[PDB]
Length: 6
Image 1: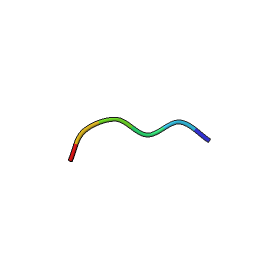
Image 2: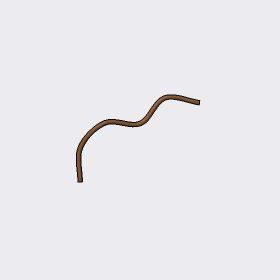
Image 3: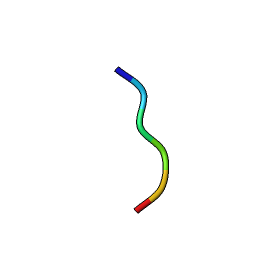
Image 4: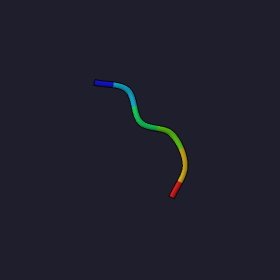
């Protein structure tokens, strides 16, 4: 699982 941002 990989998550970037906001």
